[PDB]
Image (spheres, coloured by chain):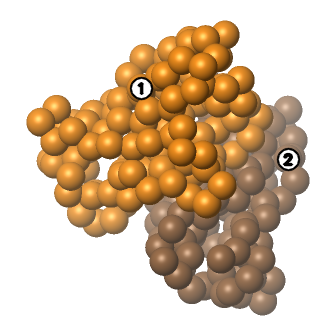
Chain colours: A brown, B orange
Amino acid sequence: NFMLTQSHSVSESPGKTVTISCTRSSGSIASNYVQWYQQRPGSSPTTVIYEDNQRPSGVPDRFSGSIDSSSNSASLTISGLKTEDEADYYCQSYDSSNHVVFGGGTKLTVL
Amino acid sequence: NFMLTQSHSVSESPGKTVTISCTRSSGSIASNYVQWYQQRPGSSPTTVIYEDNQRPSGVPDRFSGSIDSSSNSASLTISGLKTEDEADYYCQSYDSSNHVVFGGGTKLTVL
Ligand code: NA
């Protein structure tokens, strides 16, 4: 139905803030919930954001999700970058038949 | 919700058949659809099985999914193993709030 195009891999110093973006290619980004997963090297994906901006229990408030209707994108912002945040991040949403669509992933390196 | 516990990583020769399993920790495996994703080295997850046993277009019939209610498990079988099948494989399902639950992943190494 569409693809989710994520922003380029980024490097950032500890304590800083980084924002990763996820652009839906057709149809409104606001038409289906966006989730964000963190996948640390060698590990499995875990939710950091679901329903656009909800944090699961145990995910700290340094993580926040947003939706920008004008750019048809979703964004994940991580402030207070810790070296434990070094991971590949994936945005994910659903098409009309409720099939999962994954973004292509963004690598975050903590300098 | 529940956890999905995957079978151990496996190495197998080309042309052989491999089965990876995924056991749901509580509740009924059959109560929510199970999806399997292939994650090739350095790439994003792509669906190989959805809705327990459905292949997306372009996924070869070497891949098949099944559910075993008596062991509360799902299985992904890959016949005629190919070098291109070398990947981490993740099972995935949903809880009654529709929250996504991922398995911890199983690495398939093709010898
Ligand atoms: Na948020």
Q: Secondary structure at mark 2?
A: loop
Residue at image point 21% right, 39% down: B68
Where residue A16 appears, as percent x and y from the top left, is 79, 47
Q: Secondary structure at mark 1?
A: strand
Q: Is residue B27 above or below residue B39?
A: below
The answer to whether residue A22 is visible is yes
The answer to whether residue A14 is visible is no
Q: Residues within 10 Å of mark 2 (few under 14, many from 20)?
A: few
Residue at image point 56% right, 58% down: B56
Q: Could you tell me which chain the residue with mark 1 belongs to?
A: B
- Confirm if mark 1 falls within 8 A of ligand 1: no
To which quarter of the image does residue B38 belong? Answer: top right
Q: Is residue A49 above or below residue A9?
A: below
Question: For mark 1, what is the residue?
Answer: B19
Q: Is residue A25 above or below residue A60?
A: below
Looking at the rendered structure, whether the residues under marks 2 and 1 are on a common chain is answered as no
Where residue A97 appears, as percent x and y from the top left, is 48, 77
Q: Nearer the viewer, residue B79 or B56?
A: B79
Could you tell me how far apart the alpha carbons at marks 2 and 1 are, in whole angstroms? 34 Å
Q: Nearer the viewer, residue B88 or A19?
A: B88
Question: For mark 2, what is the residue?
Answer: A9
Which amino acid type corresponds to the residue marked 2 in the rendered image? Ser
Q: Is residue A97 above or below residue A54?
A: below
